[PDB]
């Protein structure tokens, strides 16, 4: 499978034709204020330099594989472990966030993928309610350089070739996300890639994260994908809510 | 294991000492109104008179086995099939509901136990979040005989001995539940019996169902339990919310 053409995702995984797919257009107007939604709690995200983490050009994104010990709670009794993070981005002044807000696409998006503590493996969790949870943040153009993002972006050069990887030092993974853990949208959706399994709890932060133009350019212009093609516009088209209600943690 | 006697439950099933157990004290004023909670959908619940259904004294409750085909939705793509229903009740002047509202215990409680359609078997769903869903309604005293409940309470005679069972005509299962399916409390919790597995989505109807004082009496005073002693007070004490916010479908 690939972005921008065949093989039609459904022929790959039938679940890519489910009613309740991701990503979606967030309309904060139509969101439901749900005061049950307490602030997110991350444990063990402040990693030391050793051991090193694998960073991979898998042809679809750049993926940072995360070690055991990153614990995430969406609430009391809603416990997850981080597996990996990856990025979706566009090209030169064409934005590439997967989620949009009142139809606005942001320059790029980060996903931190998590497995419910009730499952030993991802393949058991696919399609199961709340089996995976994604924490999602938009990246916008800002004046300053994001020093946290610079540690990953300075290594893209080394994995330019599709299917290539490198080892990088541990870092503050929670410094790749916004500081406001209390203001977010939450909804039930799917993977945005095949096999597109449903049952995924998406949390999407109100606050964005700022990268410099050089940084956004480095993300969009450095990696190569399937064929002699640049790895760009690595986002799926927005999917109708089909009667899902997005919750908001704030009025 | 037994109700009222011994042994401490955490000694049969350490899971009974989890942080996120059921049943709980509902405080409607501390509940969080979430507009995302849609009306419950129950299809296939109007059973014909044949086939007949197994009704069984299992020593802990009276339990009706439900056939395949009772489909239930808590929200879009969040579907369930009904397995069984059973009751909790008090005795001669003591109320015996499991859930309580602002401390008030009601005479009795009906639990309709469902399996998520994302799992083939109950044993796979146990401990998984949303794996099992219970529809719970308080039974209280009113002036009229309840036609729906009479179909069950009149057959208790024939199964008074622990372990005895009987076949009963098909009935309308939706007729044992309250009037307004848009009005409920919901929280994540546990089985209220061993093994006290967590991940159970509890939905408690705001509105109650009315049984004649004769009928409650038939329910509390007909059945024989473990030993040469009566099947009565078959409820678990209220359990702490431990940070869990009970949600409401209504302001
Ligand atoms: C086979 C590699 C495909 C690349 N996709 C993902 O890494 C991926 C993306 C998302 S997203 N964009 O919804 O946030 C999510 Cl939630 C998970 C994964 S990978 C884990 C899921 C999976 C299991 C088995 C095969 C393929 C994917
Ligand atoms: C072995 C004792 C059986 C008595 N309890 C139940 O049938 C039962 C009660 C509840 S409750 N009060 O939370 O609604 C629920 Cl949600 C399920 C069951 S039976 C299905 C789960 C189970 C599997 C294996 C052993 C025991 C229970
Ligand atoms: Zn993604
Ligand atoms: Zn019960």
Image: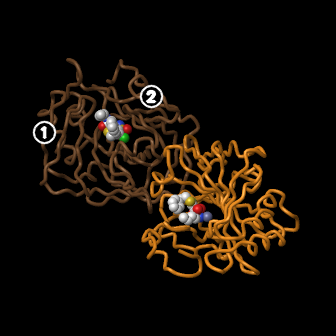
Chain colours: A brown, B orange
Q: B18 left or right of B239?
A: left
Mark yes or no: residue B240 visible.
yes
Mark yes or no: residue A139 visible.
no
Mark identifier at residue A14:
2
Other residues around mark 1 within 10 Å, as few (<14) / some (14–19) / many (≥20):
some
* Coordinates of residue A210 in the picture (x, y in percent): 29, 43
* Coordinates of residue B212 in the picture (x, y in percent): 84, 68
Mark identifier at residue A166:
1
* Coordinates of residue A205 in the picture (x, y in percent): 40, 48
Q: Are marks 1 and 2 in contact (CB under 8 Å)?
A: no
Which element is circle 1 on? strand
Q: B172 left or right of A51?
A: right
Q: Quadrant of residue B23?
A: bottom right
Image position of A227 with respect to A163: above or below:
above
Q: Quadrant of residue A213?
A: top left
Query: Which chain is home to disc 2?
Result: A
Q: B54 left or right of A127?
A: right
In terms of image quarters, where does ligand 4 lie?
bottom right
Q: Quadrant of the N terminus of chain A?
A: top left
Identity of the residue drawn at 22% across and 52% down: A67
Which of the two labelled residues, at mark 1 and mark 2, occupies the earlier sequence position?
2
Other residues around mark 2 within 10 Å, as few (<14) / some (14–19) / many (≥20):
few
Mark 2 C-beta to ligand 1 under 8 Å: no
* Coordinates of residue B101 in the picture (x, y in percent): 66, 71
Which element is circle 2 on? helix
């Amino acid at each position: 499978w690939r972005y921008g053409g065949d093989p039609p995702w459904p022929r790959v995984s039938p679940a890519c034709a489910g009613r309740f797919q991701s990503p979606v257009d967030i309309r904060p107007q139509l969101a439901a204020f749900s005061p049950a939604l307490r602030p997110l709690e991350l444990l063990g995200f402040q990693l030391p330099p050793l051991p090193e983490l694998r960073l991979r050009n898998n042809g679809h994104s750049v993926q940072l594989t995360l070690p055991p010990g990153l614990e995430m709670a969406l609430g009391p009794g809603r416990e997850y472990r981080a597996l990996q993070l990856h990025l979706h981005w566009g090209a030169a002044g064409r934005p590439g966030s997967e989620h949009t807000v009142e139809g606005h696409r942001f320059p790029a998006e980060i996903h931190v993928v998590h497995l419910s503590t009730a499952f030993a493996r991802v393949d058991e969790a696919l399609g199961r309610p709340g089996g995976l949870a994604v924490l999602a943040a938009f990246l916008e153009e800002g004046p300053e350089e994001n020093s946290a993002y610079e540690q990953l972006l300075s290594r893209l050069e080394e994995i330019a070739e599709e299917g290539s990887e490198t080892q990088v030092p541990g870092l503050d993974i929670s410094a790749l996300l916004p500081s406001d853990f209390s203001r977010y949208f939450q909804y039930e959706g799917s993977l945005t890639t095949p096999p597109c399994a449903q049952g995924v709890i998406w949390t999407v932060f109100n606050q964005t994260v700022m990268l410099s133009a050089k940084q956004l350019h480095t993300l969009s212009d450095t990696l190569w994908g399937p064929g002699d093609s640049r790895l760009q516009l690595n986002f799926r088209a927005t999917q109708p809510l089909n009667g899902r209600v997005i919750e908001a943690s704030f009025p």
